[PDB]
Image (cartoon, rainbow over all chains, first blue to last red):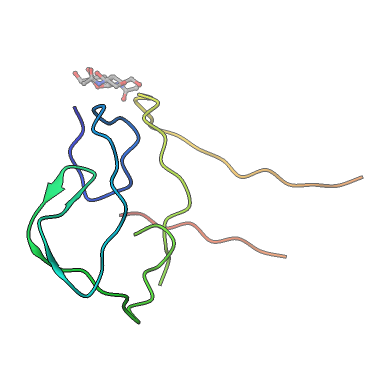
Length: 49
Length: 32
Ligand SMILES: *[C@@H]1O[C@H](CO)[C@@H](O[C@H]2O[C@H](CO)[C@@H](O)[C@H](O)[C@H]2NC(C)=O)[C@H](O)[C@H]1NC(C)=O
């Protein structure tokens, strides 16, 4: 199994929720489990990141 | 500064290369 910060292409069958913002939540992005306030950001990621 | 374009998990054990030219300019080669 390749584990990297690059875009994932194989995933387990976990159902995606909606996205909730400006509120404290227990998130998981492609297996990236954490906890925090998700909010829209002016950080212009390059298209490969 | 050069961003990525491509990655190939293609398993070649490389030692050599060349460019290709189109006909009916200059190029430069360095090492890492
Ligand atoms: C990768 O391919 C090369 C051939 O293209 C293999 O051979 C090279 O390395 C060997 C290491 O023992 C040398 O014995 C060979 O003389 C050498 N050949 C050339 C032309 O450079 C190499 O073994 C391959 N890699 C692995 C890990 O086996």
